[PDB]
Amino acid sequence: DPVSALSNDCIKRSLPVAPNIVGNEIEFAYAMAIPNELGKLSSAQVVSSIAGATGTYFDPNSYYTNSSGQDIPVKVCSDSQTNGTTTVIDFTVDTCAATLRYYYIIPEEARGKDVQFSFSVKASNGQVAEYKLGPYKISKMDMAKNLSVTNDKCYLSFLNEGEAVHIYSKADLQANPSLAAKIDIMYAYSEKSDLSHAFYTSSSPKEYMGGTELPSGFVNNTKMIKVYGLQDRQLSDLQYSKFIDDLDFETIDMSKCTNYILGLKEEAGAWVETADGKYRAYVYINKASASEVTVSVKRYKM
Amino acid sequence: PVSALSNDCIKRSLPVAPNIVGNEIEFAYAMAIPNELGKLSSAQVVSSIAGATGTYFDPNSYYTNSSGQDIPVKVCSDSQTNGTTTVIDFTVDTCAATLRYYYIIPEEARGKDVQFSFSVKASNGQVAEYKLGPYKISKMDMAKNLSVTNDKCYLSFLNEGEAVHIYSKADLQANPSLAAKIDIMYAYSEKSDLSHAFYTSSSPKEYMGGTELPSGFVNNTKMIKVYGLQDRQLSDLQYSKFIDDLDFETIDMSKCTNYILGLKEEAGAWVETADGKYRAYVYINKASASEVTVSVKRYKM
């Protein structure tokens, strides 16, 4: 026999190796079952230990599996409601068994902390069940994906709050020359393909800059280590990848660093440490053509 | 890869099980549409001979868990049948469902074939359809779980549409003409050699333990006692044993008798009425000193 009463089970769908980054979701599959002759499912709830950001919800579909292992969503609930730590959803369709997906959107206040979860269910015979998961570690990292870099949109800052990188333009600096003090890296493309796509910093040698000039006020001397083919599954969305996590930032050796990088291209990368040692980052080149580069960045505050 | 509304249907009733008037033919009708394109709107079945009252689609879709057990999810409102057509509407959004349809076999289908056309509509305007049959309907009649007692003791296999009818002693006192319709008289004796017995016009006195036939009981029914034929439709047990029309046509009644003693649970009897008009199988569902429960399949020769 299986459980002769309301029962439950819950599995984290998000991968154990994948770091839990602010702004991203942690996804759970919460299964409930009651013998059909005893009653039907009434409601489900999750209480998180730190209130989720806006967008934390239960999807109202139960996901049943066909013979081929593919999902069949059936809309068995009304919309979820979240107040602070607690998300509740009501069944509006009679069923004895369902699996609902819960999405916790990681809030700024969880950065660097642990979060745990208590899932629970009610059925129409007055029975209840409960299932706890966690704690789970939330990363200190920030991440920004698929940002556009061009000869005009060329000034990378790793110093803004909550922003792994920000790309300032030449227009931004003409308007607000003070922004030059926040700039860590200047991108330039040269048609000499010994220079090609380049990252420069305050002390880059004039010899390797192919005519590019730093704006006045660009005084940060950023440390950089050029890499190729170091892929991160979150930054590149290509599978069988590994993940850069907090410990990798803590333990990267920045001794053998340089003050310029030449020949960037798709899949190239750069480990970065800002002038004052305040932040480290990894800049990944998703794509690069003569007229545009796309970058994605993880940043970690030391 | 499904790229459009699609369907499939399987008959769930077993091929070996005869399709008998009053009973159901059950079908599992599966439908699916890619979820991004829309959702299931409605399902319909048209039978070639209008089903009897009770023909319906169960409003639950049956999904299967990992353990292979059904999960019923109430995704439709009640079905409606008008004549040959049963229609049911989805009231819950889904891209895939399996609904069970039950066709209750009407009298007018007896000895004929019945076929089926299933169809589905989705919210993108697409349709799909699937045909099954024809399926043969039996000529048999079946009556289950009838009460036989020392007073409710006169079995007639002669009534229209009724596999067996149990007349009582009070029935015969009120309507003496009923004796002419009686094929078998049941009696229980406390002599363990006789026990629960069936008798007929020529049963020998010596095996009747003092039971007497009423006057007018003139039919000499042919009988053969059977062991080990727990017909599934008559018994609701697990044995995969089914008496069908051909078995009645071809059963050898040469070595018959005119009485049966020691009836008990799971025993049975092949019967041919005096005029050869009907053959039957009487199954003993259970027996106590005070009451026998019988179920009967009858076939008109």
Image (cartoon, coloured by chain):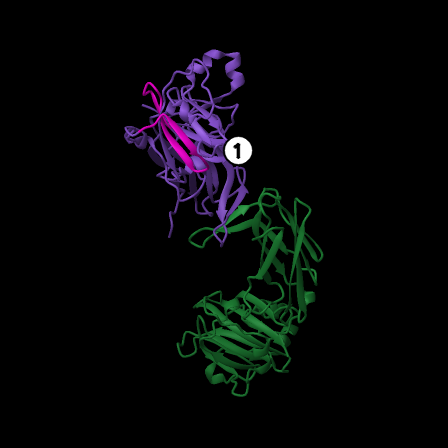
Chain colours: A purple, B green
Position in image of residue B87 (x %, y %)? 67, 51
Q: Is residue A268 magenta?
A: yes
> Label 1, on which residue?
A290
On screen, residue A28 above or below B149: above
Range covered by the magenta-colored residues: A257-281
Residue A141 lies, with reference to residue B234, above or below; the image says above
Of residues A254 and A297, the one nearer the viewer is A254
Q: Chain of mark 1?
A: A
In this picture, is B141 found above or below A74? Answer: below
Give amino acid for label 1: Ala
Identify which residue, B204 or B262, lies in the foreground: B262
Q: Is residue A136 left or right of residue B217?
A: left
* Residue B93 on the magenta span: no
Query: SS at mark 1?
Result: loop
Q: Tell me, yes or no, if residue B19 can be seen here.
A: yes
> Eyeballing the image, is B58 above or below A140?
below
Disc 1 crowd, CA 10 A, few/some/many (<14, 14-19, 20+): few
- Residue B156: image quadrant is bottom right
Residue at 60%, 79% in the rendered image: B217
**Which residue is most to the right?**
B83
Write the residue at 43% across / 42% down. Answer: A32
Q: Is residue B139 left or right of residue B284?
A: right
